[PDB]
Image (cartoon, coloured by chain):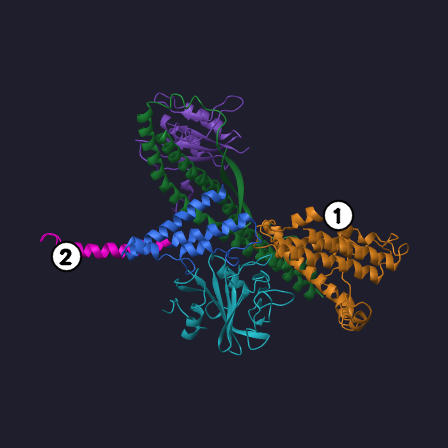
Amino acid sequence: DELAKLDAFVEGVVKKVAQYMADVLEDSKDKVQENLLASGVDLVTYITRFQWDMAKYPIKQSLKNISEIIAKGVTQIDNDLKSRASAYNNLKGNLQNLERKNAGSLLTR
Amino acid sequence: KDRIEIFPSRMAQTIMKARLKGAQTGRNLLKKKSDALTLRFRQILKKIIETKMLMGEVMREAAFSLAEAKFTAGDFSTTVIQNVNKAQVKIRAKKDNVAGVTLPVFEHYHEGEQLAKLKRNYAKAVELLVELASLQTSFVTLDEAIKITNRRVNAIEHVIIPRIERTLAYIITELDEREREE
Amino acid sequence: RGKLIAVIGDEDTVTGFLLGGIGELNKNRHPNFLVVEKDTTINEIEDTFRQFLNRDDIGIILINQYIAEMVRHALDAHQRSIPAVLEIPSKEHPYDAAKDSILRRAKGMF
Amino acid sequence: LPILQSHSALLENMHIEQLARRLPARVQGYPWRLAYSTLEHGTSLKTLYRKSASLDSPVLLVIKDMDNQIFGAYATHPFRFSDHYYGTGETFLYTFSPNFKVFKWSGENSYFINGDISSLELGGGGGRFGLWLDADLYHGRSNSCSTFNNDILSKKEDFIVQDLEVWTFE
Amino acid sequence: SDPVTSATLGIVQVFWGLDKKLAQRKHFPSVNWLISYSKYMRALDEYYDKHFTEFVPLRTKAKEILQEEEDLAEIVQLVGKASLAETDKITLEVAKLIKDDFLQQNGYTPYDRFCPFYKTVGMLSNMISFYDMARRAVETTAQSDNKITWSIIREHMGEILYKLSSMKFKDPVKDGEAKIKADYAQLLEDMQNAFRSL
């Protein structure tokens, strides 16, 4: 049960951090989806060739402790994405609001 | 009494100088205790007037929740008073220490969407109230210990040290007499 | 085990703090709340307040401030720290201000 | 391209460039904050643990010895008092000797970091430590340990700290 | 203050002072370990180095423990022990053990009419070994989710504390040097096993 909740969480963090890269790059959703990589290889190659990373996640620990190591790192990536996305979106909003005051009525200009 | 009744001798001087250094040390440690208790007392007084300015949010929201809920359901208070039984939020007493004074504190432990919103909006209020009573049981207990400590600092300064100094001045005066007789 | 919390309030803040899970009635069938309905005799809001004040099972007493004020006599007379009396706000009667029985210790300081 | 630091003192830009190429994906693109420096905060191991106690991200240790050699470790966890060894295999030792060398995990043992009231040390495998420091941050020692298969990190096995810094990514 | 005492302490190399509080509390011999002195401790240094080797470090630590407790005892009278650190509870409780079960000696009973120096060094070795282990267990579990205390040690080690406080009851006229050493060495093993098990 604890892993089933944790999978749905990290799959969501993967979808968020992928979606926000498409919102940043803008050029086309298929080109972004083609230019996703894990360890510098295509995701189909990454999954097909999987080997556990002993350094990031220790084998000789309990299944519970390994699960918590993965959960902490995913939670950090989620928080740092939220922070960076908010800070970048503010510039994008402000620059567009200056453009909206170059546009508009002779009253508002 | 003006003096400690000890009979004049170089032994009596040695004892009364040991009492003087004892009392002057006791006063300085009790002055440190008085400050350490007072620093905590002037801290939790800020926590009290701060927490009471969150009641003016969480009770408003709870009151609006109750108006909306009784408006939605027609009634509760005719029956949810009468339905009372063994019940699910309680207090465990627990302890904190400040300069060797022990302070009592409390620990909360726990045994349709509009009603669920009301249950949230009241449960988050009893989490202020069981905190604020921890601050008020601390504050009222800490005020007492400052008074007892300041009274000892005053008694050592005004009552105990002067009686030692009068005794010690008498001993020196009587030893000059014995020397002049000899 | 642990103490209860007790409530001395207008009927709407005895539905509040009861839909909040506070408060029982004991083996003797003594309750844990009082309801100051508009025709309440002034003695009642002391008569039970003294019963809470010297029971062993009550840890906190929550009182709407306007009916602490009806017993400001009996309520400021509580010098101990054993049951903590919180003077909570009410509905249309104004919120918690000055006149609180515990804050007054800091007279030259708050 | 070179990273952003909120100050610096033991590292010149050619040290920053060569370290920043090697740090893990966890900490690439984060600004570096000075958690502890003997030159800012006074010199003791109790101060180093006190300044580190609030942290919850990796750290870089930088040491200059009295022979002016620069060396240290990158560690996955802050330096804290621990009953047993702690850390993970992204930990590494490094030195500029004068060329830059980095000693990543051998895979042999997990003796990465151990902290005591009177010392801080990294590595294990018999009586060896890749890096050990005393309570004063005055004496240290380095020898090859099988956790990292490192060289001597200093000019000598036994050395005196000239100055020391702990950086965190935050 | 007396002219005879003032003249005598200008001459003699050893002085064993009394404490009237120890005498009134019927602690014997009533010797004051904070005003007594010997000026032969450097002269005897080669004898202890040749014949005993272990002792001078034990004596040194014992005199530190007894002075540290005299510094603590003046303050706990004012502020009632509640602020006292676990190392300092450890210090008071070993100072009591030394005072009551080493420095106290009944001169009118077969086992302690005369304490030989192997019995003396053995008892002090075990009490100072307990202090080293007990203080290490407390310090080495500060900054931890599980923290050792004097009370945790006392609850775990009451039979070791009973054996230590009982080391004085060995009779050197009935029990040989080899037996008394073997018993005291078994108590060190029992201490080490008990602390390793904590």
Q: Is residue D145 magenta?
A: no
Q: Is residue D166 left or right of residue D85?
A: left
Q: Nearer the viewer, residue E117 or E196?
A: E196
Asked if residue E21 shows in the view, the reply is no
- Tell me which chain appears cyan: D
Q: Nearer the viewer, residue B55 or E72?
A: B55
Image location (x, y in percent) of residue C18: 42, 29
User: In the figure, C95 relative to D151: above or below?
Assistant: above
Which contiguous range is marked in magenta?
A81-109
Asked if residue B173 shows in the view, the reply is yes
Q: How many marks?
A: 2
Tell me the residue that label 1 is attached to. Answer: E159
Image location (x, y in percent) of residue B11: 70, 60
Q: Which mark is residue D134?
A: none
What is the chief secondary structure element of the magenta stretch?
A: helix
The colour one sees for chain A in the rendered image is blue
- Tell me which chain appears purple: C
Q: Is residue B78 left or right of residue E75?
A: left
- Observer-side mark, 1 or 2, equals 2
The colour one sees for chain B in the rendered image is green
Image location (x, y in percent) of residue D59: 48, 63
- Tell me which chain appears orange: E
User: In the figure, D55 relative to E48: above or below?
Assistant: above
| SS label for mark 2 | helix
Quarter of the N terminus of chain E within the rendering: bottom right
Tell me the residue that label 2 is attached to. Answer: A102
Query: What amino acid does circle 2 point to?
Result: Asn
Q: Is residue A88 magenta?
A: yes
